[PDB]
Length: 50
Length: 49
Image (tube, rainbow over the protein chains, first blue to last red):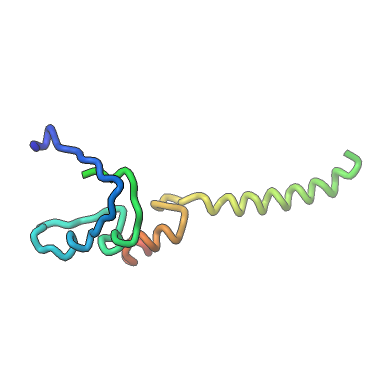
């Protein structure tokens, strides 16, 4: 979608492997603010939104 | 209220301990007041801050 109508998707009831996002070189910017990128596999979340 | 002088000292000491324990719940401007949460969420360069 365009930036004025940005698409928001809820993520819930799943086990997430974030290691495929860090180890992928396709992303020019992979920048996390309130959490370390390498600790994402060690934590549990709710209210996940993309 | 006959023994109020001793009870004041007991209440002051217990209240000082309760305030000192309560102060652990404050984050003081950090992201969290829990050290385990910070150590499990952040890399050491920002977890140090």
